[PDB]
Image (tube, coloured by chain):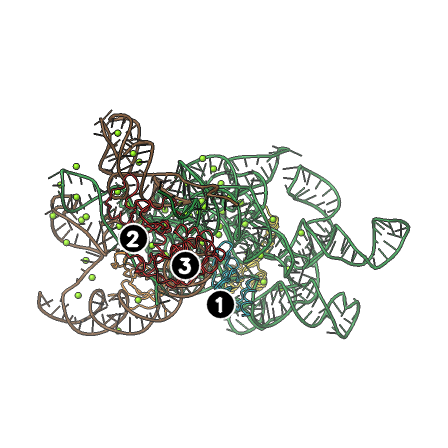
Chain colours: A cyan, B orange, C red, D yellow, E brown, F green
Amino acid sequence: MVTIRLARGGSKKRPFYHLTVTNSRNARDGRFVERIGFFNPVATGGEVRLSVDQERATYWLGQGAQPSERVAQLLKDAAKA
Amino acid sequence: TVRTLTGRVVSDKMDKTVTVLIERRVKHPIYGKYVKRSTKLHAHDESNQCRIGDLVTIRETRPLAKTKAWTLVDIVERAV
Amino acid sequence: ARYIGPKCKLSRREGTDLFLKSGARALDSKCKAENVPGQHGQRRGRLSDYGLQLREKQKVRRIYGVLERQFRGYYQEASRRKGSTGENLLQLLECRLDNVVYRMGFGSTRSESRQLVSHKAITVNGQTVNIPSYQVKAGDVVAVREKSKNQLRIAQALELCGQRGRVEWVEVDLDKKAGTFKSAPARSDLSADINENLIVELYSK
Amino acid sequence: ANTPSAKKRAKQAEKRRSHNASLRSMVRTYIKNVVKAIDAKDLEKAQAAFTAAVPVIDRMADKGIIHKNKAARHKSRLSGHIKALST
RNA sequence: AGAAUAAGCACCGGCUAACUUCGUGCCAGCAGCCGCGGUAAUACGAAGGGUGCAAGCGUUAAUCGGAAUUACUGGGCGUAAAGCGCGCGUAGGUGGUUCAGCAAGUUGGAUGUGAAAUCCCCGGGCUCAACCUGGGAACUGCAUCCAAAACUACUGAGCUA
RNA sequence: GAACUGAAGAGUUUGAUCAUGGCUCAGAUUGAACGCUGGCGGCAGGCCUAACACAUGCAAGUCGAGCGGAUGAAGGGAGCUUGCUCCUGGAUUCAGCGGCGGACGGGUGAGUAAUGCCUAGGAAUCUGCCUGGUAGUGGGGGAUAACGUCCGGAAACGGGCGCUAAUACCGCAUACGUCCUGAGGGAGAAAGUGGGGGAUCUUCGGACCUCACGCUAUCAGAUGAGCCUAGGUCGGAUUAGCUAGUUGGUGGGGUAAAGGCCUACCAAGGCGACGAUCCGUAACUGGUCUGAGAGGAUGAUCAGUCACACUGGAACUGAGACACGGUCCAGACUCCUACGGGAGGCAGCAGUGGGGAAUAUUGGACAAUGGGCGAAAGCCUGAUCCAGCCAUGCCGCGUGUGUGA
Ligand SMILES: [Mg+2]
Ligand SMILES: [Mg+2]
Ligand SMILES: [Mg+2]
Ligand SMILES: [Mg+2]
Ligand SMILES: [Mg+2]
Ligand SMILES: [Mg+2]
Ligand SMILES: [Mg+2]
Ligand SMILES: [Mg+2]
Ligand SMILES: [Mg+2]
Ligand SMILES: [Mg+2]
Ligand SMILES: [Mg+2]
Ligand SMILES: [Mg+2]
Ligand SMILES: [Mg+2]
Ligand SMILES: [Mg+2]
Ligand SMILES: [Mg+2]
Ligand SMILES: [Mg+2]
Ligand SMILES: [Mg+2]
Ligand SMILES: [Mg+2]
Ligand SMILES: [Mg+2]
Ligand SMILES: [Mg+2]
Ligand SMILES: [Mg+2]
Ligand SMILES: [Mg+2]
Ligand SMILES: [Mg+2]
Ligand SMILES: [Mg+2]
Ligand SMILES: [Mg+2]
Ligand SMILES: [Mg+2]
Ligand SMILES: [Mg+2]
Ligand SMILES: [Mg+2]
Ligand SMILES: [Mg+2]
Ligand SMILES: [Mg+2]
Ligand SMILES: [Mg+2]
Ligand SMILES: [Mg+2]
Ligand SMILES: [Mg+2]
Ligand SMILES: [Mg+2]
Ligand SMILES: [Mg+2]
Ligand SMILES: [Mg+2]
Ligand SMILES: [Mg+2]
Ligand SMILES: [Mg+2]
Ligand SMILES: [Mg+2]
Ligand SMILES: [Mg+2]
Ligand SMILES: [Mg+2]
Ligand SMILES: [Mg+2]
Ligand SMILES: [Mg+2]
Ligand SMILES: [Mg+2]
Ligand SMILES: [Mg+2]
Ligand SMILES: [Mg+2]
Ligand SMILES: [Mg+2]
Ligand SMILES: [Mg+2]
Ligand SMILES: [Mg+2]
Ligand SMILES: [Mg+2]
Ligand SMILES: [Mg+2]
Ligand SMILES: [Mg+2]
Ligand SMILES: [Mg+2]
Ligand SMILES: [Mg+2]
Ligand SMILES: [Mg+2]
């Protein structure tokens, strides 16, 4: 199916993640159709931990896209805020 | 609103088909002067009403044969 | 890296101010600082335009103790920055951490200021910074360690720099061994003898 | 092969081939009988062959041996030929 | 605890920043181009002394620049290379002047695209930088429509240089 | 609001001069190599040549909630005794059938000058797993693997006979959706497993109600793929003619789909100095390096598309392959053999020989992000995350400091 998961940008031992809506039969950071936001596992200073776009995510879920487990946790945590 | 293309009939010796020349003037990529290029297309003339020299307007459709995917919609000028 | 060697042979070659000693006695009565070094020293040696560019570029580099890869990076950044790159280069090169801890009066020489800054004895907001290239943003309170405030080398450097002039844009509290930078210096503030335009002429070729 | 799943897939494939071949032969047999019925210029036997051939054709189309558009095309063309023969 | 423990390479006749002596004597050797050397060589080989870069320094191979030296921007052809020996003419290029129409070129606007990254501008994080990253700008391109009619093209009717 | 703002010349033809004109130089860059020398850290990069041949080791499995079979513990009890066996039960493990995955991820650039790539479009198509609706999941049968037995073989194993299971296979039961048939009528499917339970027939064996997974027919949505048209895509004219399935039509065949895609007849058409055909060379693009710009060179890293998988062909399985560690045939080269016959494909990650001026370890773990499988624990992952060697590149810091005639 088409699924929403994490693409690993950043540098060695300094991760960064793009929340990508990709066809599941693609590479980790291969072609996609749309990007909804990002997650920063280092934060610190004025850097924001996570941000997403709500309306596009709702559209993608309304078109039946399976989010990964970590992506599901982070999106529900963001929806809490 | 069909995407037409206007042209001049060149040869029609094949049954239910017509050859149309379409002339365009393209700008040279560097020297800035326009040169007249031409394109030859084959169109489906169902009732072979197009003789040589006529000026017509065609339309894009699905392929009717190999290298024949246009159909004339109506003649707009005849020939002497 | 860094330069090691005689600190007045350079002055003799260049024949100008070229601050490289503590300045205890004078600038002159150490090395007869009017002749270029070596056997062939008395000759004035009239030199072409390329000589002019090379001589003043070496002058600025030696007074500020910067290597040439770093210096050319500085020049590229200055050219990137808008508004008359010639003085942008000086303004940006002035904001180095070691030259600030010198000009704030905490060190006898640029080399001794680098000595202090490298061995982790100076702060910016309490955070250990020991890179003698840090570009100090305006506002930061540069200070020495509360542990290091009792060292006598800082005391002697401060009393020696007590009579060297006033820059009239920083606000320095001397009791606590702290500095403060408000806004970047203007072109007129620095010594208006060496021109900046001849450098940018050198690097535009 | 090297991985045992490759061997299992292979043997299941020969089993599936030996199965599918018989049913493809059966459908081809029925349409061939129908076609030679029309080409022989007889109507009643053409009717009977068509009525006896459509059920197996459609059952096989649903079974997944052939694709449904193919079966529909066969039905339509053969019906057209017989209707043309009717006159 | 201990300054302890960690500087090399090229060059110095001009172009190009930096000179003296000793040894050979058109030999041995140098060299990117001009070129040095035959008994005081700042050019050879060494010494001292300098100049330039620096954990690197040179050398070779390759691309663009300088080269307006393939010249659209932006060159030339009497004597430096360069006008066919000379006509006629096919395709092609170019077209005196007036009135009117059309709207292909032309101009302005709207809409869709021009994947992401990279380039550019303003910020954020690692002691700074390299590096990572947010937002924006840009991607001169292409297609579809709406409006204008000065010039070119197309259509009709004229005029005489 | 900011997105740029940018352009240098010198030496050398002459006794000397001006012009023309070639050569050389000062800059920025390389996946670079060589010589002298050598302290450290961070981030990157690392067979450009022989798509030359390859030792060993690893790089795709998973499901007992699909199915028989065999492993059957702990035990509630008994016998004789202290150990075993057995009734009833029973937690684990898997050879085989079956369901998914293996067509993804990973590698290379040989071929390819256009069935490839880039830009803009359009009409005749298909699509598992995902989501949203709709209608159902009833009743039978014949086998077979494993399992015994016999023959044959060096092995892979092959063959004869007997029996068994299902979500394996095939009829039968009907058609809210569908297919064709002009209205008329006709045509076409399903598999059950796991958790509970009020009442009822009854061995709440089961029937019955619920939930979970799963299965069938269909509409739509995305996701992915197939097909068509116009424009652009290296050098050579010391390559000027090429084409007979070739160009168009009719009937039929074929594909999921338009089409000379295939076939039989009908006519002689079609392309080309706007460069057809032929020869050489070469994956294409975003982009990279230079330049004031216009341009010039180029396609290392990363991303999108294409092609290939020892060489040449062909099809089967499926939703999708002409299939990178699948099948069959032929070939070249290495190997085993009981001489009957068999085995192999590092352009997957380290490694070796060789070629070269020259490019590295036969290292760790699923800890994280993804992938496959299962409902859930969980397994597999040389993809990925980290280590090793290398001054290869960029950036940063050290080899100290003051005085000292
Ligand atoms: Mg350095
Ligand atoms: Mg049936
Ligand atoms: Mg079916
Ligand atoms: Mg000089
Ligand atoms: Mg030399
Ligand atoms: Mg001598
Ligand atoms: Mg010498
Ligand atoms: Mg040029
Ligand atoms: Mg050149
Ligand atoms: Mg000229
Ligand atoms: Mg002459
Ligand atoms: Mg003449
Ligand atoms: Mg002529
Ligand atoms: Mg003439
Ligand atoms: Mg003419
Ligand atoms: Mg005119
Ligand atoms: Mg004309
Ligand atoms: Mg326009
Ligand atoms: Mg972009
Ligand atoms: Mg108008
Ligand atoms: Mg002379
Ligand atoms: Mg001259
Ligand atoms: Mg098993
Ligand atoms: Mg691939
Ligand atoms: Mg290769
Ligand atoms: Mg060719
Ligand atoms: Mg079944
Ligand atoms: Mg084309
Ligand atoms: Mg024929
Ligand atoms: Mg036809
Ligand atoms: Mg036909
Ligand atoms: Mg075709
Ligand atoms: Mg050609
Ligand atoms: Mg190439
Ligand atoms: Mg090639
Ligand atoms: Mg190319
Ligand atoms: Mg290729
Ligand atoms: Mg640039
Ligand atoms: Mg230029
Ligand atoms: Mg490569
Ligand atoms: Mg790619
Ligand atoms: Mg292939
Ligand atoms: Mg093949
Ligand atoms: Mg090979
Ligand atoms: Mg093979
Ligand atoms: Mg199939
Ligand atoms: Mg395979
Ligand atoms: Mg292999
Ligand atoms: Mg390998
Ligand atoms: Mg080797
Ligand atoms: Mg060798
Ligand atoms: Mg995981
Ligand atoms: Mg394994
Ligand atoms: Mg290193
Ligand atoms: Mg080296």
Query: For the residue marked with disc 2, what is the amino acid?
Result: Ile
Looking at the image, residue D2 lies above or below residue D41: above
What number of labels is visible?
3
Q: Residues within 10 Å of mark 3 (few under 14, many from 20)?
A: some
Q: Chain of mark 1?
A: A
Q: Is residue D11 left or right of residue F270?
A: right
Q: How far from the left and from the top, in percent, is residue F278?
A: 34, 45
Residue holding disc 2: C199
Residue drawn at 61 percent across, 54 percent down: D19
- Residue F35, located in which quarter of the rendered image? top left
Query: For the residue marked with disc 1, what is the amino acid?
Result: Asp
Residue A53 marker: 1
Q: Give the number of the mark in front: 3 or 1.
A: 3
Q: Nearer the viewer, residue C125 or F99?
A: C125
Q: Disc 2 or 3, which lies upstream in sequence? A: 3
Q: How far from the left and from the top, in percent, is residue C16?
A: 29, 49
Q: CA distance from mark 2 to mark 1?
A: 50 Å
Residue holding disc 3: C136
Q: Nearer the viewer, residue C86 or F67?
A: C86
Q: Residues within 10 Å of mark 1 (few under 14, many from 20)?
A: few
Q: How far from the left and from the top, in percent, is residue F168?
A: 64, 57
Q: Give the number of the mark in front: 2 or 1.
A: 2
Q: Secondary structure at mark 1?
A: loop
- Residue B58, located in which quarter of the rendered image? bottom left
Q: Nearer the viewer, residue F219 or F270?
A: F219
Q: Chain of mark 2?
A: C
Q: CA distance from mark 3 to mark 1?
A: 37 Å
Query: For the residue marked with disc 3, what is the amino acid?
Result: Val
